[PDB]
Length: 199
Ligand code: NA
Ligand code: NA
Ligand code: NA
Image (cartoon, rainbow, N blue to C red; front, side, top):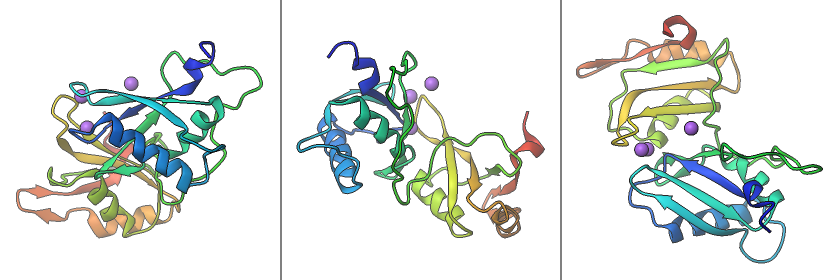
């Protein structure tokens, strides 16, 4: 249906270099099924359009409700990268239909890290570390509620700093103690609440 198309599409950012539309479709169709999010036989994702130059994709789903459920995959790791899943900017919630996902996907860590009391900044990361490896560094201290590694939009290369929020706010000081000042060749990690050094 044409009226619901805006409510059946999602933006996916930070996609792996060189990924094909078929590989992305298969990934999401499988994850939807394995996660218990798919609501009928057959594929929930109908199509994927990739903008290779600009590093983003749009997924199109067969139903409004499956599209909403797929928002729960925000931050899922695909080929080392934390996929950013968002509504299209022109999306308008429909009457009587839900706007937010209802099913949690175990192990998936959101990419939305709002400014808050215990949001952490991690600066000085080696630029060869992908999203997955930086997530593992941080998860050593405890489970994350949210995380984003900052990249150069034109090249896709890590800018060497990230933000995060732990599930347990009390882990924040443990990560600071374990990581702040750590020396890595020419780099020295700065790990502190992001409010301390925000511009
Ligand atoms: Na990227
Ligand atoms: Na880009
Ligand atoms: Na945007």
